[PDB]
Image (tube, rainbow, N blue to C red):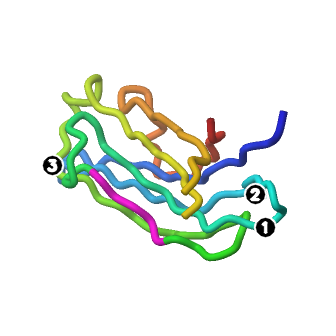
Amino acid sequence: QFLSGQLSIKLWFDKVGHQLIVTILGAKDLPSREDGRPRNPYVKIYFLPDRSDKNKRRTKTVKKTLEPKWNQTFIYSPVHRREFRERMLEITLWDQSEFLGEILIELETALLDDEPHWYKLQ
């Protein structure tokens, strides 16, 4: 019915350094609030399993926008190629509250090409 917006994310795995680099660039086309005002958006990421603080990261919250730009790089470590079939990134967007959607990326087929890509929020 309504557009939900998209999130630009860049992923890369450093196979020698055993680290997964996740850069959450920005979002576009976020839905306004029902009252017409813009959002105060942030992104939360869990590298699962273990839903614990160690595996949790969050962007800062941008004030009053539908096109936030965070440009933040998160570093997960230690990470091992052999673990990819059993790891996923749970990426959620929030209006600081209201849930604005989720992108769930399985590591085994993730775009680990160090390029930015757009993902639809669900």
Q: Which of marks 1 and 3 is in front?
A: 1
Question: Which residue is at a point 61% across and 51% down the rendered structure image?
Answer: 7
Say which residue label 1 marks: 37
Q: Residue 33 carries which label?
A: 2
**What amino acid type is highlighted by mark number 3?**
Pro
User: 120 or 38, which lies in front?
Assistant: 38
Quadrant of the frame with the N terminus: top right
Please state the horizontal and vertical placement of residue 96, each as a whole percent of the image. Answer: 54, 64
**Residue denoted by label 3:** 78
Q: In this view, does 83 lie above or below 21?
A: above
What secondary structure is marked by label 1? loop
Q: Position of residue 122 (x, y in %)?
A: 62, 35
Callout 2 crowding tier (Cα within 10 Å): few <14, some 14–19, many ≥20 = few
Q: What element carries label 2?
A: loop
- Marks 1 and 2 in Cβ contact (< 8 Å): yes
Q: Which residue occupies the foreground of this view, 116 or 96?
A: 96
Separation of residues labelled 1 and 2 (CA atoms) = 5 Å
Q: Which residue is drawn at 68% across and 65% down?
A: 39
Q: Farthest top residue? A: 85
Could you tell me the amino acid type at mark 1? Arg
Boundaries of the magenta span: 56-60
